[PDB]
Image (cartoon, rainbow, N blue to C red; front, side, top):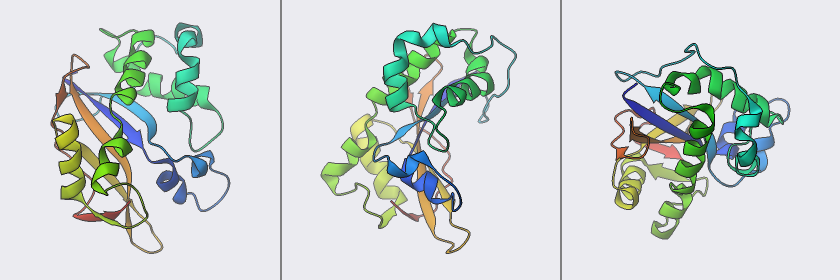
Length: 190
């Protein structure tokens, strides 16, 4: 792999697309971790053969993980961590074992406070229209590089909502680099 995509999601927006059934994320008011995806040639590496998920290897991080990496769609956190490790984590196992991988994600989250970067410039979430250029600019100002913005379109109203923010990292897992792909248009609701 040549880089990492550190993906954070906005729980309320994510759950807004679940028009049936429960969605624990409906009540969260902070960006949470979706995942840390190893990349190669502008594409996500997935389902690499590797070690099976082992909860005892990340036992010392259970408090941080339950707070920062909750399953927002269902009330089973461990299953979410297991799914993310098997689908993405195994692809960077040659240099980051399971314990270091989850620690990386937690550290990244603690060092990339999205709302904290937006709040002072009146760009915090308020269910109103925001500009892709403005949001990317504010984040670049605070963190030094351009983030990747991901959106989803409501099938009923055709309105676009910001659901995830990506921070791109070099393969060392600490050097921030510019992201180059957004799925958001010029404007979206946040």
